[PDB]
Length: 217
Length: 217
Ligand SMILES: O=P(O)(O)OCC1OC(O)C(O)C1O
Ligand SMILES: O=P(O)(O)OCC1OC(O)C(O)C1O
Figure 1 (cartoon, rainbow over the protein chains, first blue to last red):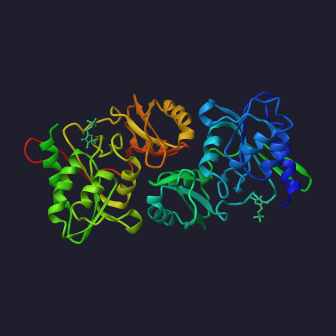
Figure 2 (figure 1 turned 90 degrees about the vertical axis):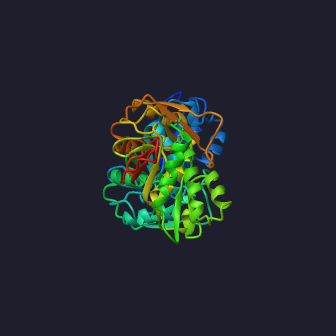
Figure 3 (figure 1 turned 90 degrees about the horizontal axis):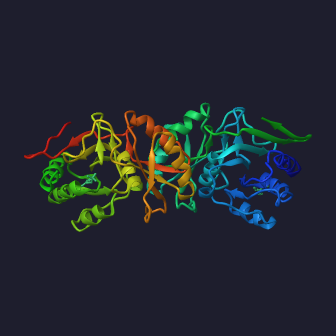
C-alpha cells in the first residue's frame, strides 16, 4: 500500500499502551511508526522487549530500557505487523523477520496488536509462503513431510537463523484450517517453529486505510 | 539390570539388519553392545546413520561408512533404547543422549527397535524426568506452561545442546495420554523438541533377561 497508511496504524497502537509498562515490539515498516509514537512516551513506561535486531536499536535511540523474555512474567501487549492475516485474525508471520523470536514474545504477551496496511488481509492463508524453521540435519525429512501436507517447501539457501537452523518457505498450500495446520507441522521432528500464528492470533487488528486507521477488536 | 543383559540385548537386535543397507544407530550402554555386533557383518552394510557422537566414532573405527540424514529417504531400522517405555510402546527418551537427533533419526527409520534392561518397562510414563529442548530466550515461559500441565520442570544448568539450546527436565507428571502431552508440548513456542516418542514409538522391544533377551515383534 502506502507508508502514510502504515503510519496511521502504527500511531493508533499507542492508545493500547498502558502508562508505566514494558512494551512488546515486533519488527517492520509499520512497526517503526509505532516506535516513533513510543518515543513520545519514553519517560512514561518501564521498558520494552523486542523480537527485532533493528527495533532494539531504535528503542535505544529514544532511551527505552530493553528487557529480555526471561526477565518478565508477562507483557501487556505485543505490537507487530503480519505477512498475511485472515478474517479469523490468524497470521502468517516470520517471512522477513526472526520467526522464533516473534512467536515467543507473542505467546508471552497479553494482547497482540496487529498493525497493518491494506495489503496483509487475505481470504485464505498460503499464497505468501509459510516459513518453517528446521534443525539442519532434518531439512530433507521435514521437506518430504510438508509435501505430504500439500505444500511446495523451498530451502531458503544462503542463510541460517541465529539458532543456526534453516528455513523452508512452503509455497502453494490453501490453508483452510490454520489451527490444525500448526499442529501437524508442529508435530514434525526437526521442526523448530512454524510461522502459522493461528493458535495465538491477533487480539486487535489495526488496519491503516485511505481514510485513517480502522481498528478491529 | 546388568551389563551382560545389555549385551545379550544389543546382540539380539543384530538379526534385524540385512545386506547392502544403511543402519540406524542410537547411543547407550546397550547399543554399544549392538555396535559391537554390527562390525562382524560390516561388509554387507552400506554403512550407518546415527544420532550420537560416540557411536559415529566407533562405527567409523570399524570401517562403517557414515551417512547423513540429508543423503537418505529412509532407513530400514533404528536401534536405540529408552529411559522409559509403556505397554503401548511409548517411550521417554533423551535424558541421556541427543534428544533432537534421536527423534529425527527415528522419524526417517521405518522400524524402531528399543533395546532395554529390566529397568525400562513402566506402566505410566513420567517418573524418569521428561526432557524438553528449549530456545534459551524462552526458558521461563516454556517452564510456566509446563507447570500448568501438572509439571515441575528443572533447568539442566551448566550445559546446552550442539546448537546452543537449554534443557528442561520435568518431574512430578503422570503421563497416561502421551500422544496428547506431546501434542501439547510440541505446541508451546520456544519448545524445540520433547522427549516423548508417542506418535512414533518402539516397533520391537528388546529387553535383558538372565539368559538371552526377551524380544517382542
Ligand atoms: O524493495 P522493497 O521490497 O520494497 O524493500 C523495502 C521494504 O521492505 C519492507 O519489509 C517494507 O515494508 C518495505 O517498504
Ligand atoms: O537408569 P537410567 O538413570 O535411566 O540410566 C541408565 C541408562 O538409561 C538408558 O536409556 C540407557 O541406555 C542406560 O544405560
